[PDB]
Amino acid sequence: PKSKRARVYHLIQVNKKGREAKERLFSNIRETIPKYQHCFVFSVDNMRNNYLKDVRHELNDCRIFFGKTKLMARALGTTPEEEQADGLHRLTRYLTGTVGLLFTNRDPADIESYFSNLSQVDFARAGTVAPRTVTVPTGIVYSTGGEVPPEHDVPVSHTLEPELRRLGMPVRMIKGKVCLGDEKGEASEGYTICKEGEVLDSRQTRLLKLFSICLSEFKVSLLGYWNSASGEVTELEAGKTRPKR
Amino acid sequence: RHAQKIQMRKAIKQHEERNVKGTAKALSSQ
Amino acid sequence: MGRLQEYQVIGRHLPTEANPNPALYRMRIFAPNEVVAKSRFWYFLRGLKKVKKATGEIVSVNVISEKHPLKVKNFGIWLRYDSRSGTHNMYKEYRETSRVAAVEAMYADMAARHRARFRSIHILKVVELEKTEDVKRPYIKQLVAKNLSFPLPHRVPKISTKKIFSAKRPSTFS
Amino acid sequence: MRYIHSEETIPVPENLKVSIKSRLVTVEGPRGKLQKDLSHIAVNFSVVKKGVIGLEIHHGSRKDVAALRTVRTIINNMIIGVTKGFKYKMRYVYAHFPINVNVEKNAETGCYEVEIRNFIGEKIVRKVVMAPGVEVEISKAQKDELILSGNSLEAVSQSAADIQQICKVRNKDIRKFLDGIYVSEKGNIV
RNA sequence: CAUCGGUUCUGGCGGGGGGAUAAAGGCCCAGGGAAUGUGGCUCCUCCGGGAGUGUUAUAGCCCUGGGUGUAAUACCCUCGCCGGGACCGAGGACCGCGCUCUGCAAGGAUGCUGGCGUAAUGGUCACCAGCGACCCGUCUUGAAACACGGACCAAGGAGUCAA
RNA sequence: AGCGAAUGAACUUUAAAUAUGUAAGAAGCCCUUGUUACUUAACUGAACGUGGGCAUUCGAAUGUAUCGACACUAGUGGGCCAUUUUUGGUAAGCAGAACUGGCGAUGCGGGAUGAACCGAACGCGGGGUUAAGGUGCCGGAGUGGACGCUCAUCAGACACCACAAAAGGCGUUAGUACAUCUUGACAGCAGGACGGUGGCCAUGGAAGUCGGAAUCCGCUAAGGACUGUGUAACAACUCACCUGCCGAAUGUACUAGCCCUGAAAAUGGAUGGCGCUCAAGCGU
RNA sequence: GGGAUAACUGGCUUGUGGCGGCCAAGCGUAGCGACGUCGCUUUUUGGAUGCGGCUCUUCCUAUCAUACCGAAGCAGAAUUCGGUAAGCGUUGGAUUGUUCACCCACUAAUAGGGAACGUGAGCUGGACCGUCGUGAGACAGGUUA
RNA sequence: AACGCGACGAUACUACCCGCACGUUGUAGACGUAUAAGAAUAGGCUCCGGCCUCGUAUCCUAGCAGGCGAUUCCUCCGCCGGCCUCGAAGUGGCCGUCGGUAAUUCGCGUAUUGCAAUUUAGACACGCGCGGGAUCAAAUCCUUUGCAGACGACUUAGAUGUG
């Protein structure tokens, strides 16, 4: 009845895709399966995954899928009777959560070497344990939060001032400059954003992203793969300790 | 509020149409 | 309304030389008594076909009673009621022991919720839901919920209305 | 539509003790003792497991079940207050006149009095009395800041709002005069 | 107070008929069906309570035909029999209709008994109480409203006589 | 109704509702032949008569507290309101005809009150039962029963006419249609929201967001030559869209009840009053 | 000269114009149609009015001031709009037959109304006939509320 | 509040208080006029066993309108004293004395009011009587005053004194 919230009808140019997009996903996976010899299942547990585009550009000659997990599972087939190819159903069993497919015409050892040598620094992300203590210096705060030398740094922005306050540093606006305490220092002590060995909240993660300080590492973890010629799936170390479907 | 809701409904309908899609003054002036 | 019973009426146009042995129309209705049953049958037949009271007769009127008035049934009533805007359809559900009780409750509920009266309500089809999965309304769903047990909190005691004064403050627990 | 049964559940920590009378709720723990009357809402309190309390409404309406969501969060707020407590960090800023804040506790009535002086040059002293059970301090961790902590979230929040309202600017430009005492951080002591 | 007549109000009891010769329901008989699944087994953060396979099993239920049965009952309509109360008693030899005919509840109340036999019943004035209740006449109008006359009492006071 | 009958309100086999005129027997119809100054080619027609026919259901029902004719005599010549039908008109009012009904000259019960409403007409009494209307006493009779709805910062208690609508409610209940959901719906939280590209023109400067026009491609899970915040420009945030967690029903527009608003002045007062909230309000 | 009509408003009044086109939910199966927008009034350079006026009582709020709020380039000062509020106060000059407008002055400001067809209480500043003319009227002619 | 109330002083007469003889005295109306927890109602009570819809409960209730006498009973009731208690518009308990008293049973009387006729029977209030204690007053008028005043009214003063 009445006493209900009214959601805004957005003046936008893109709308929700839904079933016909799920259908393109089905068609693309089913047309991709026969074209390649090996299918890898990889996992990206707690990473921002904005480096997947560079991974794609590097493996331009490989077809990588990262969609909704249940849709990918059912496109691959969940039962031995609805499989497109033999055993893609038990590869669906490795396909459990924040995972992706990788169809290749290449050698499993070369794929594993690439994704074992590939590693890039990324922002903390919520839930990760802090590997360090990051505290801002007392005084005028800069755009890096006292990580690069201050003499080679630019002050943080007055439009990030109110956002920085809502994230929780007692910082003030003196003469157009954001400073913690007083401009000449003294005043107050520093603000320790994160402590060693402590689960980081989204507040702290947003603080770290605003200060452009990276604490986490992006690494794709290959859970397993499947060769079509033998019709056989091989487990690479990861799935013995990662929960399965 | 009647005028405002009529305006909002017209704006919503016009936006839906345009998102789906991919003289008397002259005589009087003379 | 009142006390009702099922009344099944067959009536036919009066025989003539042109069309002997007429169609013998029949329908089942709800009336407090047989006179009202026949009047409603003739009104409905005038509304549907081109047969009138004067040019017709009542072949039979019988009371349909329930097959099993002792077992709890769920009834779906599809009805049409005319309000100030026009004619509107409703499907409503009632948990009773008889189609008579279902229709009684339906008249009462329509009067209470929409101020629709007897000549403003038309009974189009009353059915007994043969099994669950045929109930669509949350109240009868919660009535047919498994292992249904509930207390009766704040039960006002039934004191005689001539007992003006009491010596103890009454309790509302049992 | 007269729902036959609607149930809610509140879990309890190991180190707390909840004693609930007809509709009085009393909670004890490491931090202290909090009591509240809920006699204005119809509810049956129950135990379903070792460490969870249950709240139910029979033959109720959506208003009744909505009360059951409020009754839970209020009791949950009391449990959190007795386990970890509540704390409000407030900051006072000024442009030309330093705001002088004096916090003391009187032996009589056992309350905390906060006195504000020199709010944009006013000669009037502004005295605010705290609700009982509230501790107010000027912490030497940051300058121009105050910490108001306690057991009851309602009392702590109402006290913070009381200081914020008493330091209000009148007949001036809101965009120009930026002086006052404002709630900056909200959280728990532990 | 008892026995009666007239009118009337209000309780109980005994049958009859009808209806789908109620519908149901109990109880046997046969045939199907299913779930808000009667036991078991598997799993299950085990005082406990749940998910899965599992249809009469250590509960039952639904539908259909048959019997018992011309069952019971409700409901509608009917034929009677008892109880309590109220108000009334008109007429004054016989005739008449009758019946249950030594007689009678049959064309209208008699029998028995008590207190008092006087303000006791009853009636009239004054007041109280409950309810009810615009100040009369004239005039106009469809009607009101208005207007007119009315300080009180006594006597007089207005369709008569002749052609 | 049909046009699988023809033809096309002006079509019809048939035929509604609704009021309405005439007639329903001895106070009769005919048939038959005598007259006539009428008439006809004519005992031929018309009128005046004879005979017959049914006296019993003699020519439907129902009522019938009698009807008709003559003579004489008194008071009367106004209208008002309303239903239905009907003509005209206005912004709305309203005006005019016809029928019937209430008032006169009419008392009584009810509607608190009252020309125009509902019931019912009248000698004086006793008893019984009802109408309209009522049963929280005032006030005789129910704080009767069954199912629901409603909380009003002067509700409502029969006014439904006005204000007044395609009106305003994030009040509440019932319903209709359409759409999405274990191929994970609504809401949320943690993340992505990228590249050609500081896309073309203009401006001192304008990079998606002071302006004009087009408004594409790739990667795709998806991302607008961008929905807002922000910079002098950047930058940065955010939205759109997408993924992971959660887990089962949601959510858009209409409809129907009751409720709030939909306009108010001036001595202090009115559902009759007190007062009434699972009512002493509304519907059956 | 005759006839009808013979007072009249009484949940009346108040802030947002009318005409035509487009659009338009319903209804309806063409006709009706709200809100908006466009065209006319309407744009490219900054006197009207033809019964009035004083003292006192009371009421309304449709609030001028005083009190408190929300918004505004609201720096301060002075303000503007709007909300709750009637407790408390609430004018004078010039001109005109009078009134308002405009203007001029103090003042915190110097608001608008009701006392119910007699607009609080008190006070002040004609129609009928007759004669004679008819292209218009006259009468110290008569009668009368 | 001149028809709301409280505290206190003095109260001559009258009879102020006390006991009964009562009243042909009044009463919107005796006839067992019997009964104190508080508080909640989505809870409570308790003797701590348990109990709670239910005041259709508890107390009291026999005797010539309630006589007289016994076996037996220490239970109930009332009046006076003492100690305390109750003030929202004022009472109850404990002790004591004194009087009455079916928990059981029995005896001697009831008649005749004549077949019903309010079973005149309670309380408070008021009034006449005795015999016991006690008390022994004011106001108004008059004169005067002027803190007052239309007239009334009001503040004052007249008994041996600061008159």
Image: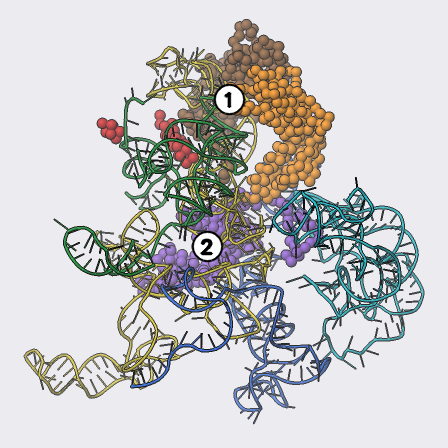
Chain colours: A brown, B red, C purple, D orange, E blue, F yellow, G green, H cyan
Above or below, F78 relative to A122: below
Asked whether residue A72 is in view, the answer is yes
Foreground: E78 or F270?
F270
For image coordinates 42% across by 59% down, the residue present is C41
Q: Residue A128 carries which label?
A: none
Residue type for callout 2: Phe
Measured as percent of width and height from the top left, residue E55 is found at: 58, 45
Measured as percent of width and height from the top left, residue C64 is found at: 49, 58
How far apart marks 1 and 2 lie (CA) works out to: 68 Å
Measured as percent of width and height from the top left, residue G41 is found at: 28, 32
Foreground: G28 or G114?
G114
Foreground: F85 or E78?
F85
Residue D36 falls in image quadrant: top right
Above or below, D152 relative to D179: below
Residue type for callout 1: Asp
Measured as percent of width and height from the top left, residue F63 is found at: 39, 76
For image coordinates 62% across by 15% down, the residue present is D143
How many numbered marks, from 0 up? 2
Asked whether residue C77 is in view, the answer is no
Query: Subunit of mark 1?
Result: D
Query: Subunit of mark 2?
Result: C
Foreground: E134 or D35?
E134
Q: In this view, does A24 lie to the left or right of E9?
A: left
For image coordinates 70% across by 38% down, the residue present is D21
Q: Considering the numbered disc 2 on the image, is that residue within a helix, a strand or a loop?
A: loop
Please name which of the two marks, 1 or 2, marks the residue nearer to the observer: 1
Read off the residue under disc 1. Answer: D173
Read off the residue under disc 2. Answer: C118
Q: Considering the numbered disc 1 on the image, is that residue within a helix, a strand or a loop?
A: loop
Q: In which quarter of the image is the C terminus of chain D?
A: top right
